[PDB]
């Protein structure tokens, strides 16, 4: 006997999967699978409009490229332009249908149902199409209604995924740019600030941290030197090496960074503040500003020390050429359990190729 | 016709996917569940690590209601992770009939299931009440509610993630904007309030809600370029001479240089505000003497909000101006310092500005 709630439970499962999925590619796949099962259709496609190239596009299969579609032509094109629904009982009798794809593969397209996708402001942003009704000779008025509800859900999900990626990007950008507010008085580069978080992301990941903490270290580590904004110019701009009085002030960039960052409530800022105050501490207990030792330094500060020293060593600094991989490796092995956490150093060494790769393509 | 509940689900999940507010997500989910389970009432209880209680919200948008995490039906399900299916609440010893008493309600059937996060921990309880057959929730109803519960878990975890990100993003922008705090007196609350005034101004001038959210977050960064000003200028313990003042004026250009290496709309706007905020509608400002609409609307809105905040704060010998005095100054400056059209909008809403100033001292 059949389950009367079968499709309902199937739809709820798809909706759970989709709500969890941040990648637009897979959202599109899951929406397509959903349509096929709910519409009882053999094939389904989503076409979205590209502002720049002036084309609709679709992904044909799992993992394959964007196929551009002519928005001025065909069935999807009609629906995209007019906002009207096309329900084709026989594709081979509609001059808007192209048989070439059909001609090559042994596939026979019979029925086509295409509806527009609308954004929140009722603009047409694409088309949702289904092909070859399996359990009836034609798509019905009821099928049209159902596909329109699916379209609304698809629209919302697609926009949400895009809005979220826009936010994610803006958040990174802001952290990167503001972290480099020191650019006028300190020579550390914008790419340095980015790369340090990227190396620390690998370390946290390979060290087995939760995906949330991996993401936080990537964004928190770049802020470690923000405290330099409060250092006097006579110290920060001194064209050589510091006296005791001056060095003592320079060290306070850690304390200052902490003061700038600690007033947050977010985990991001609590971790960033700790990194700011910890990143010159040594596994030894011989670092600054407090001589914290071993596990007294949060794992985030320990990961940032390794990443930051790595990136400095692999850049040219006046009087000293950037070190190559081999020397950097020997250095880290020698400083294991001294400057750096011995467990994290091993992880870092084991992933040293990914480190140099980031360094090479982000100059 | 069995497609009825599918169209209902699809309507609710569309609204859920748009919703940025946890409270509203929860209301949608409970309305979804009432319709799909054909039950009269539903509730979602979530756990607060801090207070060690469950909580729930009721409709109309009232306060969070604290619920005892140990005793009760919800309490039982949260602690044990077991499903609870009650045919008659008034015969169950764990039922608290006081909710019925105050509301005029008579609870009959209760079905309550756990909500789990991805990590697999129990984070709450989904409860459905008064199946509309006036009879028991069935094994098939339990099974349906297990699927609804997984969908609720996912959308709730997603909405919480989204709120964490938004809050972290604001925190970052606010804290780093105040990185000037060792060397400049502009306060943390000032930096926040200026975006909040510009947010009301943008809304009331009819910008898209996305742009309104952008101005709230972009305006706060407009003085970041002060970090590039030499100490012999910024910390000079005497009035600046003309040459030093020309250097000080470059904090606009410096802010632009810090911010402009973006691709995001937020940074593109923030960079414009950094470079424009001392420009004057009549073209007599700095650094470039831009005039009227040559100044982006975002820069024009920030100049109004930043001056407002400064007129309404006390300094030694210089008492904050009151509403009447501030209004008069803005009318005088219409078409001079400020965009006449925006000033009108700002003046129509000045009570909202004073309320912000009073709420965040
Ligand atoms: Fe450094
Ligand atoms: Fe440092
Ligand atoms: Fe560094
Ligand atoms: Fe200022
Ligand atoms: Fe300024
Ligand atoms: Fe200001």
Image (cartoon, coloured by chain):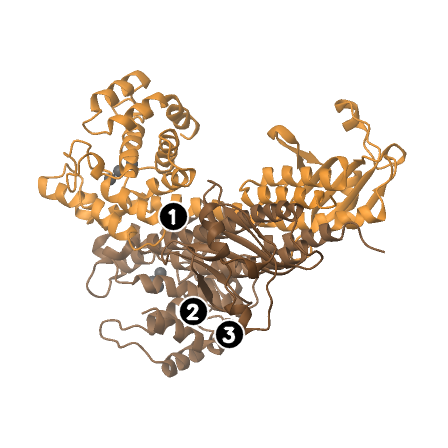
Chain colours: A brown, B orange
Q: Which residue is mark 2?
A: A306
| x and y, in percent, of residue B207 in the image | 37, 35
Is disc 1 on the same chain as disc 3? yes
The front one of B137 and B122 is: B137
The residue at 31%/54% (across/down) is A228
The chain to which mark 2 is attached is A
Between discs 2 and 1, the one toward the N terminus? 1
Can residue B220 be seen here?
yes
Can residue B115 be seen here?
no
Packing grade of label 2 (10 A; few <14, some 14-19, many >=20) is: many
Q: Is residue B203 left or right of residue A135?
A: left
Between discs 3 and 1, the one toward the N terminus? 1
Real-space Cα separation, disc 2 to disc 3, in angstroms? 11 Å
Q: Is residue B344 left or right of residue A304?
A: left
Q: Is residue B329 left or right of residue A226?
A: left
Secondary structure type for disc 1: helix
| x and y, in percent, of residue B3 in the image | 71, 46
Packing grade of label 1 (10 A; few <14, some 14-19, many >=20) is: many
Q: Which residue is mark 1?
A: A260
| x and y, in percent, of residue B97 in the image | 81, 29
Q: Which residue is mark 3?
A: A347
Kindly identify which numbered label has been placed on residue B351: none
Secondary structure type for disc 2: helix
The residue at 22%/44% (across/down) is B252
Real-space Cα separation, disc 3 to disc 1, in angstroms? 31 Å
């Amino acid at each position: 006997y059949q389950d009367p709630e079968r499709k309902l439970k199937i739809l709820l499962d798809y909706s759970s999967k989709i709500a969890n999925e941040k990648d637009l590619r897979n959202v599109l796949l899951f929406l397509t699978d959903l349509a096929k099962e709910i519409m009882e259709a053999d094939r389904a496609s989503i076409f979205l409009y590209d502002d720049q190239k002036k084309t609709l596009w679709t992904i044909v299969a799992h993992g394959v490229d964007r196929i551009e579609i002519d928005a001025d032509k065909g069935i999807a094109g009609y629906v995209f332009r007019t906002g009207e629904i096309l329900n084709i009982p026989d594709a081979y009798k509609d001059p808007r249908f192209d048989r070439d794809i059909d001609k090559r593969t042994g596939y026979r397209t019979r029925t086509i149902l295409a509806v527009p996708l609308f954004d929140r402001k009722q603009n047409i942003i694409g088309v949702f199409q289904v092909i070859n009704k399996l359990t009836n000779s034609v798509f019905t008025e009821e099928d049209i209604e159902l596909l329109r509800h699916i379209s609304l859900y698809a629209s919302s999900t697609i926009e949400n995924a895009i809005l979220y990626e826009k936010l994610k990007k803006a958040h990174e950008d802001v952290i990167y740019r503001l972290s480099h507010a020191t650019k006028f008085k300190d020579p550390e580069t914008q790419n340095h600030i980015i790369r340090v978080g990227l190396y620390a992301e690998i370390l946290a990941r390979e060290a087995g941290l939760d995906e949330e903490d991996v993401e936080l270290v990537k964004l928190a580590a770049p802020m470690h030197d923000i405290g330099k904004v409060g250092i006097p110019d006579r110290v920060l701009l001194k064209p050589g090496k510091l006296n005791d009085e001056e060095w003592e002030i320079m060290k306070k960039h850690t304390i200052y960074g902490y003061e700038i960052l600690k007033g947050g409530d977010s985990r991001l800022l609590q971790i960033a503040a700790d990194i700011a105050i910890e990143h010159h501490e040594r596994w030894d207990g011989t670092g600054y500003p407090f001589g914290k030792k071993g596990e007294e330094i949060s794992i985030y500060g320990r990961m940032t020390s390794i990443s930051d020293v790595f990136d400095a060593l692999t850049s040219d600094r006046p009087y000293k050429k950037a070190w190559d991989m081999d020397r950097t490796v020997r250095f880290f092995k020698e400083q294991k359990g001294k400057h750096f956490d011995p467990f994290l150093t091993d992880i870092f060494l084991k992933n040293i190729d990914q480190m140099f790769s980031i360094k090479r393509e982000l100059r």
